[PDB]
Image: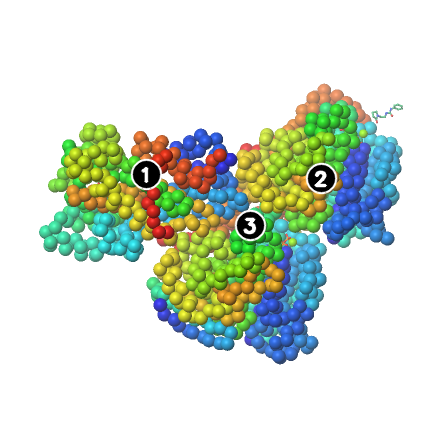
Amino acid sequence: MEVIELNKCTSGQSFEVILKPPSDPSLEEIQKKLEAAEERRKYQEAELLKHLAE
Amino acid sequence: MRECISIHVGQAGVQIGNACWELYCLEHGIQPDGQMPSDKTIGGGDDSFNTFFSETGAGKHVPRAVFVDLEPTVIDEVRTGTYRQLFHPEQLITGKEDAANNYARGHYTIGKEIIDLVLDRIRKLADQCTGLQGFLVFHSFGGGTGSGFTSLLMERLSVDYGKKSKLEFSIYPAPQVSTAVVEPYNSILTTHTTLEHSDCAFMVDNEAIYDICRRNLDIERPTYTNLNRLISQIVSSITASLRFDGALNVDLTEFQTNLVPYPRIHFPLATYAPVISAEKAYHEQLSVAEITNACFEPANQMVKCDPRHGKYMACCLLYRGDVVPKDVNAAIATIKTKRSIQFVDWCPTGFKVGINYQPPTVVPGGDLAKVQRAVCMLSNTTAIAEAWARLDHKFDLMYAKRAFVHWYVGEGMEEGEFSEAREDMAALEKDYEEVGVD
Amino acid sequence: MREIVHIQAGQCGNQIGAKFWEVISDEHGIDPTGSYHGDSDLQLERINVYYNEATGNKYVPRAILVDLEPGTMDSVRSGPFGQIFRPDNFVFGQSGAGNNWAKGHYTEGAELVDSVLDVVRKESESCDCLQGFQLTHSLGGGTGSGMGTLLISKIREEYPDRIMNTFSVMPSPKVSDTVVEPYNATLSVHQLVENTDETYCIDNEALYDICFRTLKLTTPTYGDLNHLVSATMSGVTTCLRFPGQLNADLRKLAVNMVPFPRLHFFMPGFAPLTSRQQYRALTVPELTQQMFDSKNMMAACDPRHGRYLTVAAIFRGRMSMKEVDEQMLNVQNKNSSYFVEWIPNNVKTAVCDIPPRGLKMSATFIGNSTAIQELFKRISEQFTAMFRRKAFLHWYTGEGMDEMEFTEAESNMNDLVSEYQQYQD
Amino acid sequence: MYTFVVRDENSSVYAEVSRLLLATGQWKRLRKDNPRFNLMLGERNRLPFGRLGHEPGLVQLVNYYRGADKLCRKASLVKLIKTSPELSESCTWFPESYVIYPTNLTDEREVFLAAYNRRREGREGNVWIAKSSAGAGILISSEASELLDFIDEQGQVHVIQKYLEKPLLLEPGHRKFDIRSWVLVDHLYNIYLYREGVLRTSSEPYNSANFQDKTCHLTNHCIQKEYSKNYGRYEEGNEMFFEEFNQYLMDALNTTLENSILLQIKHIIRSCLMCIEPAISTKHLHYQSFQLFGFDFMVDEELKVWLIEVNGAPACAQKLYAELCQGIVDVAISSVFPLAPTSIFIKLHHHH
Ligand SMILES: Nc1nc2c(ncn2[C@@H]2O[C@H](COP(=O)(O)OP(=O)(O)OP(=O)(O)O)[C@@H](O)[C@H]2O)c(=O)[nH]1
Ligand SMILES: Nc1ncnc2c1ncn2[C@@H]1O[C@H](COP(=O)(O)OP(=O)(O)CP(=O)(O)O)[C@@H](O)[C@H]1O
Ligand SMILES: Nc1nc2c(ncn2[C@@H]2O[C@H](COP(=O)(O)OP(=O)(O)O)[C@@H](O)[C@H]2O)c(=O)[nH]1
Ligand SMILES: O=C(NCCN1CCCC1=O)Nc1ccccc1
Ligand SMILES: [Ca+2]
Ligand SMILES: [Ca+2]
Ligand SMILES: [Ca+2]
Ligand SMILES: [Mg+2]
Ligand SMILES: [Mg+2]
Ligand SMILES: [Mg+2]
């Protein structure tokens, strides 16, 4: 039951108590993912307009 | 002094952000028009509260915050609310139609078109920071904006602010206050893409905030106001170390050092006490031991689960009010003798304690009563993996039939991203069991 | 400012559409002249979802009236609330459709559709943010069925990423004008399967049986049937016309109700349904028990023959929300065998403070049930009974159609029934 | 109308409890994967406790205490007794035991040999028994070399505890036996003891000079009905119920079952359950727990009771299924979900 690193200031204090010792995607790659999904929407909508033209 | 920028995404992030900044002002003595009498340095100064507020020549204290919602109804409340004067229009960004509770809609269809705008506004705040620590991001799991747009914002922030820390405050979905059936989908989708980008995430289960309102505050049918005012008390307790003089959790880096030994397991459980109904005739003020012991009761955890059947990796006691270190250690002694607190062998069995003498500030007219001492415990327990299990199970039920998947594929998302995100969660649950169970 | 464009086509569509605007105009405090005279701010909070605001504070329904003969729309204009509709929004021909899908979809209707899209485009071009469209029509006639679906086909082509919603009156031999109604309905169902996101199925037999057995109306009329439709249409659109966060817009509604693109046909319901013992107060448990009774449902499909994929309940009136939650959970926890277990929390509930005109508190029921396949099964049998002898086909071949097109619509709806069948197990 | 699910088709006890629930007309059984249930009769292994208590409006109840495995596992019980101050290493009613890991994998190998060598020098009886939870697989030997080598041949953890060389023998027969007690702990943590117990007796005369033939040493119902040639000789199915055992203790020993054995049994039950109450109690938990336990005891010629093991998913005597299962519905299930005596239990009051 040890206390360590007691820090005291005007608005309080802090300390540690021990009971027992122990034993990313680039900007390019993010733009591709976004444009790839935008392209899949474009293709799906194209097939719908193609369907409606028939 | 180092600055902290807060970002509020979606309806949940914005309404919770509203309640927190309302509280931050009452705690620092900042009036709704931004004026702060106690601040003697007019339009400047590197004080502890200046991590969350900048200053203008007129002496206005402006929250270092950005609000983002793909629909303008929720943010218009801020534009015409009590603290409409605190913010300038640049800080409030609103689209015209939301993500329809569709992760893919918030991340891809709509997110692609507005991301560059949010980052620009965010960069404007960064340009006032002489030493930016990082970001605190408020958002929900279930919403299409909070889940879908947040994950994209986090990915870009890691590219623009590589060395900066990023913490989260995430709302875990609860059916009692949810009418979206696909929230398990969005939650697991946004946890997959954000896991490698978030340094520390405090989850709040609406189910837990809900019962605490009915049980402790005797609120028969809690509203978002009731929930958010209580949530902002916890958030206030967590962020106090950044806004006040002190030596524990003084910058965002310390949150990861003190709470996250392994990166993927970065979801500390929060437990708060006491919560007392202001409508009470008059309550008997609890002691240090009593509020400390309450930190090991499931009934006041932000996420319902059983820490007795997990293993602790870290533990922080944040006290506010009449509390001296002598009382903390005495209470801790009597809890080890009566409580099941199993630490991992590769971590010391101890507690970090911070004490701020100013007791909790309550919103005048709110539901919470003024108390002389409160505590918020931040502990990293494997027990919180129960929440991932619950959520993953619901995911499995719907996805087994591909129910609702067409709404996501229809917004340009590939079906394979579902299974990809689900396997990540299966690994996350696995990491937890490897650390806690024998 | 999420605007919805309303379109009513044909006889049935315009008479139900008329009563619908009559009912909600009263709930928003709008008089027949478009002037507001309500007493609550909640009445105008979401007023721009169905009404445009003109000079002098006038509110004009955002509705387009379509028909291939003038008759019905002359009654609307001379009706009580007729003066409220935008005169330019009356689009009508003179030949009629002779209860003929081919005339509404290919010949007579094809001649008039473009001019209807000129008005549709005009109303949409003045929307701050267009949610989507709602169409009221019958499937058993010629105009609302044939031209109605032709309009949906051409509206999707111009607004592909908006929500398309329909209130579709399905025909029944027990309440029938002509014997070709199964032909017209089978041709439209395929259109709706492809080109709508939400279709509220309304079986005229359910309306008649309710008026007869429940409401104790000796000799029901189309007007009595339309009174129910009005009240039901007002209920299902409560989410859209008042402050709320549950199913607030059409897309969010679809996202929560349509787990599969083609299975988007809903069974509506309404409680209370009392004959004139009408002044008795109705309790929350009663309101909930009735709302789920098949006799209170308007698709003439027994829900106890299928399973619910999703359910959206709306409670209107000042009541105990705590007591609403318990009764809802009680019905789910008392009959969980009729709800699929692979959609967690597939039953949602919403509350509204403003009750309908003349009720302390009511409840509207939107169910996406696999039992709806019985409706398409009845229509398919009636179709095949005549088509196997090619009976009455000359009406359609004479308009240019071929027998093949009938065989395909027949095969399409059988597929639809088979799709509902696999999810029932 | 309450709702419950069945996730353990192999449970004979809860197959009867479910049969009784449906017989009341007020409990509706749902599919084993429907979450909208009031009661769960869960599986034995990997019961998803984390998914309980999260359904709005449903008070949910399960038939297992999360964490009770600490008591119903051979090694777990040993570690629990030696580490729990409430039980202490000097526990007088639990045979001296040790946890021994096979050498192909903490471990108490040397601690065992130390105590073993002391008995070897002190001329005292030095006969131990090696057993494990992964058994039908038991070895009784007086040589430590054979007990340790037997565990290394296995790939799971075993326990070596002192073999009761002076067990109480019944007459006629000169035969060893054991006692099975059924205990039920409700959601409030009341410890109820079933008034009816059973004695699974050995149909073979106890032999102290031959631990190889494990027919007169092991009193397991399956071993006697398979390798014992006198099965069913003295009592039906090698099962002597309390009414007969009490008459024997009076005609032979001039004592009663209550005084000589039952007081000790009740004491051991409290100390075990009370010990772990702070760890498994569901008093302030989002769901509720109750469980039925099967305690196994030994009686020596000195009329001293020793704890053998605790079974978390025990079975019941064929003759007592009706009475016991019905009781479970009264104190454990209906107490939480009431319907629209002379209790068959004995409450063991204690300080929570
Ligand atoms: N605690 C709390 N939870 C909220 C609040 N608002 C919404 N939620 C929760 O958030 C989830 C829905 O996500 P939202 O934030 O409303 O959705 P969104 O971020 O606006 O994204 P959209 O789909 O575009 O509307 C539900 O589970 C709600 O319970 C709030 O103000 N406080
Ligand atoms: N230390 C000891 N002294 C004397 N006998 C012992 C003993 N340990 C075990 N036994 C004998 O073994 C039998 C119980 O074995 P044990 O309970 O360890 O195996 P098991 O758990 O597979 C049977 P069950 O679980 O059904 O009670 C008893 O009949 C007892 O006679
Ligand atoms: N509920 C209801 N159904 C109607 C009404 N008028 C016609 N119908 C039904 O609609 C079908 C006929 O379609 P109708 O609208 O008259 O043809 P249209 O004018 O060419 O579109 C028949 O099945 C009728 O039973 C009405 O006012 N109310
Ligand atoms: O106009 C007529 N038939 C048009 C074709 N049809 C027949 C079925 C419905 C329909 O549209 N018939 C007619 C009848 C009386 C007087 C003058 C003419
Ligand atoms: Ca200053
Ligand atoms: Ca990073
Ligand atoms: Ca012509
Ligand atoms: Mg939103
Ligand atoms: Mg007609
Ligand atoms: Mg066993």
Query: Label 1: few (<14), some or many (≥20) within 10 Å?
Result: some
Q: Label 2 near label 1: C-beta < 8 Å?
A: no
Residue under circle 1? D194
**Image location (x, y in percent) of residue D109:** 22, 54
Examine the rendered structure and indicate whether residue D157 appears above or below residue C202: below
Identity of the residue drawn at 67% across and 24% down: C381
Residue under circle 2? C359
**Image location (x, y in percent) of residue C262:** 65, 38
Q: Is residue B172 left or right of residue C53?
A: left
Q: Mark 1 and mark 3: span between their CA atoms?
A: 41 Å
**Image location (x, y in percent) of residue C415:** 63, 32
Q: Is residue C166 left or right of residue B340?
A: right
Residue under circle 3? B174
Amino acid type at image mark 3? Ala
Q: Mark 2 and mark 3: span between their CA atoms?
A: 32 Å
In which chain is the residue bearing label 2?
C
Image quarter (top left, top right, bottom left or bottom right) of the C terminus of chain C: top right
Query: Label 2: few (<14), some or many (≥20) within 10 Å?
Result: some
Q: Residue lying at the far bottom in this picture: please name it.
A: B41
The CB of the residue at mark 1 lies under 8 Å from ligand 2: no
